[PDB]
Each structure stands twice: as structure tokens, then as C-alpha cells.
Image (cartoon, rainbow over all chains, first blue to last red; front, side):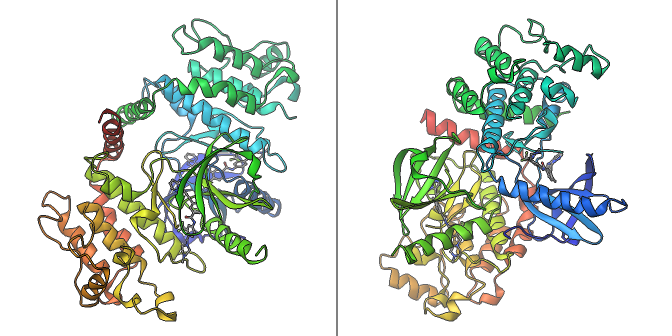
Length: 279
Length: 281
Ligand SMILES: Cc1ccc(C(=O)Nc2ccc(CN3CCN(C)CC3)c(C(F)(F)F)c2)cc1C#Cc1cnc2cccnn12
Ligand SMILES: Cc1ccc(C(=O)Nc2ccc(CN3CCN(C)CC3)c(C(F)(F)F)c2)cc1C#Cc1cnc2cccnn12
């Protein structure tokens, strides 16, 4: 009702970004708003395009109902014979995944920025869980966490199974994913790197194994290392009932975040952008 | 479509403004764990004025418009909840020279660019929204000094053809751009428009007759980047003839090349400098 319908011909300079499941994510410039945008457009040459339409409108309805500071903001729908899609704000600094694992482009990612990111992911998911009815994400991974021009988090949805809790091979799924993500953020390692076949991963996890917690994985200089290890281990407990709520997580995190002097967040970000611009 | 937030979910309320439509207070939402602003004012008609405002803000979601988070609608309490903007208004940034003694040029242009992006979006809605009360007091600044447009001495932002009220003045499509020109002059000078004249009727008369804030070396110093493109923009914007004034879409197009000369890192640096001086001074 409030959601603009954007004609395809109003979208200029389309550049590919991703080929997600049903179709492509591209960057563009809106000709009248003069801002950059992202657009997710499904393929037109499918026999199952009838249901494709339905999926797109259901997705836009969701994103629109879920407006919030840490959820990717939707700007409109494209709905024409030649072109079907969702338009959102464009996040110039890509995904958390890239931030963590492109060590040539991002050789230092200061601790405060990392805790901010974890705090904001929690704020986002928590808001979804507090909607009426609750929205459950059920596909959290670092690929789905986007970062705006100041490296604030925008949660989205588009190596799969590592973020999945064993009992899904549920109100307690997102928090499992968030624990792995947390391990991932503090370590900058791929969970289960030295492990080829993902069936072996599902088995190991079935049996209670988790990413390794180590001097090698989580070095001893991590601020609040021990509070954070507790959070991770609660979060990915074999028993879903031992895993905490996101609200409990935020409460555990708030004092950790209060330790950082506010200027240090901006300093962490300015450093990153400076190094990124030189790669 | 828009959450209804119970008053008892809002913790630690602290006064901020006693604006037009009610009191504006800061608070913390007990379940979302974020800070918020809340504007709280017949059970027939008072509601409609608030519900009409929330409908507007909700219809107008965009990067540079103040984001509405919900409505409070209870027997004890009626209001609108929005995101909270910790760095106050553009007005404070410009005129509190003790707290903010240097405001680097690039940050200033970014702000101007973003005000234009906001008003432009309003003008492009269906039907168009017209602001008609732009001033520096209504431009808010988020944690990284990005702009959020809002609405809550005054006549200086008003174009002369709106002095005589009516159905002409209301449907004027060229009001916001006049206000934006004065704001622009204000941002580049950090002077009050018409500081020298005591009585605001003499201001209305002078403006009736084509006079505008003074442009020169004292008001707009020679070191302003793109001084001459910017003076042109201001002057087209506040032209006596409404038809010579540009659309905000034209405005943005005139600005885009100016903004492109600043390396993007420079905006963040300007913001760091502010926060450092605000803290160390
Ligand atoms: C164009 C576009 C369209 C849609 C979506 C999208 O995220 N849709 C979405 C669907 C569902 C949900 C919640 N559910 C999860 C599943 N489900 C079981 C529950 C409900 C959410 C969430 F935000 F709420 F999480 C989002 C993102 C983009 C993007 C983009 C973009 C912007 N900058 C860049 C830079 C690089 C790459 N991409 N990119
Ligand atoms: C709680 C709250 C509620 C509402 C509004 C509000 O701005 N409502 C609004 C009404 C109409 C319009 C557009 N129209 C203009 C007239 N009109 C003829 C056309 C339509 C717009 C606009 F933004 F779109 F302009 C906004 C702001 C606040 C705030 C706040 C806040 C947050 N942090 C701080 C820090 C210090 C002080 N305040 N504060």
C-alpha cells in the first residue's frame, strides 16, 4: 500500500553482483531519486514463473513489515511483463563474509568494530523474533550480513549447513547460527576448514562436535574472551533448551560494548576504508 | 502495517523539546534495546491529527527522512515513536561555535546534498509531499552526521509570494527550494540570515522588494570550494521569480559534480575531527 512500484526504465547503470537462488542481484542508480540501489530480479524464461511472482510479493511484504535500523531497507518492487524484482538500499561495503576472509583487502579489523557488528546482528534478529507474529530468519550466515557505508549492519537473506543446528538435519535455530557467526567473527577462520565433505560435517555436528576453540582459533588477546566463549558455547549447545534467547544475548553484550570509548568505533572504520582504498 | 508500542515498553523518558504538536522525549525500548524518540501530545479528532502524521512519515520511508518505528495509542498516552538522533539539529551544528569551532567543508556539502536527496524524494511521491517548513531546526543528524529530515525568525526561510496566505501559497511547488537556498547560504556562512535587522516586518519588506542575505567575502569567504557554482545555485534557488527556481532534481544534478571532487574518506575524517574537538575542547 505504502510500497512504491518502480519501473524498470527508472533503473540506470545495472551491474551484476550475485547470482543467488532464483535470479540475479544487481546494483543500479534510480534516475529520479539519484541514489544507488540494489535490485533482485528473477529470470523471465522459466515455466514456473507463476509461483515465482508469488514468492517475490511474499518476500517484499516481509521486508516491508520488518522495517528497522538493522534490517535491509526495501525501497520498492519492480512488477512488469519484462522484469520482476525487489529494490533495496545498496550496501557499498558488501557482506560480513568478505570483511572476515579477504585478509589481503582487510588485514586488520579492530576489536571494537567486531563487537559492534555482533551487537547489531543481535539487535536485528531480536527485532524479528519480537514481531507479531515472530519472524524467524532460519538462514543466518555471514554472506547474509551486509555492511553500509559506515560498517553498520544490515541483515538480509538470499557453507550453508555449518550454520545449521543438528536437530534441523524451531525457535532456537537463529541463535545456533549466531554462535557460529560469533566464532567466525572472532577467529576469521572458516568453520570446518580442514574438512572436505559436508556430510562429515553434519555427522560430526550430529555427534556434538563444533568449530575448534583454541589458542590458534581464538587467540588469548581477545577482549572478554571468556564471556564470549561462554556465549558461543551456550549458543551452539547440542540441547536447544540450553541455548539462550537473543534478548539474553543483548543483555550479556551490552556491558561488553560499554567498555569501548565511542571515538574508537569511528577510528576502526576510518582505518578499514583507508586500507581498502589501497588494494 | 506499523507497530503499536505500549507506553510501558518505553523506559527512561527524558524531555528534549516542547515543539508544536507535543513534547518530544528520548527513551529506551525495553524489548528492542535501542534508543528512540517519542512525540506525545477529542478522542475523535486529536487522534486523527497524530494518525495522519504517522501515515505520512510511514508513506515517506527513505534514507534521509526521519524513520518512524511505531505509534503509541492508549487511553493514558498518545504519540509517535521514531529513531533517536543523538547529534541534534543542523541549527546547533552551525551556530554553537564554542562546541563546534571547525566544521570541515566536505561534511557541509554532504549535508546539503542529503537535504536535497530527502526533499527530492518527497517531491517525487504519489501524490507529491511538500515540506513547506524547512529550516535548520528541522534537519537532524544521526550518529555519523548523516541527515534525517523532520518537521516539528521563521519567516527568513519563506519565499515572498507566500507572505499573502491562501490556496496559491498552499499549492506552491516552489517553496521548499527557496528555503533550501537560504539554508545553503546559512550552512556555507554560519551567519544568521538578516542578523543586522531587528524587526522581522522590515525583513519581509526587503524580501518583497528582491533583497536577500548578503553575499560577499565576509559572508561567504573566497576559500569555499566551488564558491561560484554554489552562489549560482543559491541565487537561482531564491530568485524572486518562482519559475526561475530549480526543481530539487535539477538541484541534485547541479550538486553531483561538486560532491564528486571530495574523496569519500574525507567525510568520515571531518566527522572524527568534530567528535574529537567536542570531547577534547
Ligand atoms: C535486492 C534485495 C532484495 C531482497 C533482499 C533480502 O534480503 N530479502 C529478505 C527476505 C527475507 C528476510 C527474512 N526472512 C528470512 C527467511 N525466512 C524463513 C523468514 C523471513 C529478510 C530479512 F532482512 F528480514 F532478513 C530479507 C536483499 C536484497 C539485496 C541486496 C544488496 C544490497 N547491497 C548489496 C551488496 C552486495 C550484494 N547484495 N546487496
Ligand atoms: C518523535 C518525532 C515524531 C515526528 C517527527 C516529524 O518530523 N514528523 C513529520 C511530519 C511531517 C513530515 C512531512 N510533512 C511536513 C509538513 N507538510 C506540509 C508535508 C508533510 C515529516 C518529514 F520528515 F517528512 F518532513 C516529519 C519527528 C520526531 C522526532 C525526533 C527526534 C529524534 N531525535 C531527536 C533529537 C532532538 C530533537 N528531536 N529528535
